[PDB]
Structure formats: C-alpha cells, structure tokens
Length: 167
Ligand SMILES: CC(=O)N1CCN(Cc2cccc(-c3cc4c(N[C@H](c5ccc6c(c5)S(=O)(=O)CCC6)C(C)C)ncnc4[nH]3)c2)CC1
Image 1 (cartoon, rainbow, N blue to C red):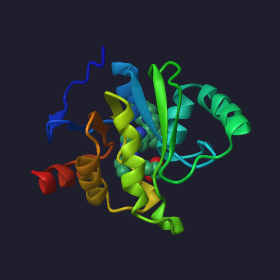
Image 2: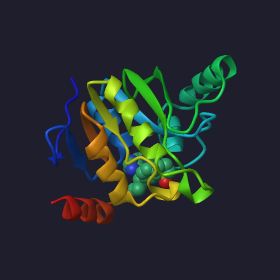
Image 3: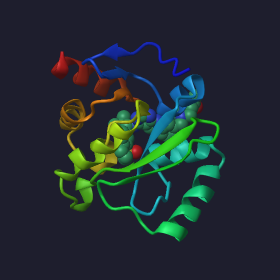
Image 4: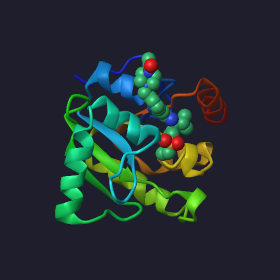
C-alpha cells in the first residue's frame, strides 16, 4: 500500500513532509517504519516514546525480549522487529547522540541501514535532543540512502529551513 501523500520530493529517492511520524504510520501503515532508537532499545522519550505509546507498550515488550537474547546494538547499527499496528516492520536505528559525545561519522553508518529496505517511513536521524545539526542530517540522508525514504519532520519551522537549504 505505502500510500504516502503530501510529500515533497527532494531527490529521485528522498521525499519530505511536515508531519508526526506516528500519525503518518497510522494513516499509511507502511512496510517499514524507522525508529530513532538507543543501543538498549529503551523507548522513554521523543520519537521512540511516541511510537512505543502508539503500540500501547507492545514495542517495548518485544524490544526487551530482543535485547535479552541478542544484547545491545552498536551506535550506527540496527535491528528489524515487528511494526505491530503501525507498520509491517520496525527498523530500529541508532544514530549518534552528539549531545552525549558520540561521533558524527556514525550518522552515515546509521543511514546505511535504510538501504536493506525498498520503502521506509523515517524520522530525521540524530536530530532533536540527539544534538546533530538537522540540515547536516538531511545532507547525510541524501548522500547515503539509495532506497526510497519518506521523511516525516514534526515541526513546520524546521521543515521550512530544510526545504529552503535543499531547495
Ligand atoms: C493529535 C495529537 O494529540 N497527537 C500529537 C502527538 N502525537 C504523539 C507525539 C508525541 C511526542 C512526540 C511526537 C513526535 C516527535 C517527532 C519528530 N521530531 C523530530 C525529531 C527527529 C529525530 C529525533 C528526535 C526528534 S528526538 O526524539 O528529539 C531524539 C531522537 C532523534 C524533531 C522535529 C527534530 N519528528 C517526527 N515525528 C515526531 N513525532 C509525537 C500523537 C498525536
């Protein structure tokens, strides 16, 4: 299905919309929804907490079972788990948190995880309280992702700065 609408195409493979990723996931029910995860898959705030709350904590129960069996992910790494009622699959991706001293080179590695899936609904990796320059995160996305990615950015002011810089 992947019925994305209202998206502005920036490149042959990158689209963007001023929207809440949770609301987009409920409407579209995409094949893959990307979560802006941490290495222990603990979804307490921001995007991760919003996606987990939309699943009524089912994402957290499943995440805890994955960590118990496989251990933590690494910064720049990912894992595929159920999307529950939001998507067929959830691709949990760990972008570097520069506000806590993690290296920005790892942002490229985090975006490279998107390439194993044909179509993804995703947030701007490492933006918000993760501390990275959001326009720089968009540049890395454009230069790294080669499959089709629909970026949901829930802030019209940020969306307008991204569309203006990209033009
Ligand atoms: C109608 C109603 O009451 N609502 C509204 C609330 N809605 C649920 C709801 C509640 C709370 C938050 C969010 C939401 C935040 C968010 C989003 N934020 C962006 C962003 C990008 C990357 C990262 C972060 C943030 S972070 O979380 O700071 C750190 C990780 C990396 C910023 C605009 C830069 N981008 C996309 N979708 C979103 N969703 C949503 C349920 C439905």
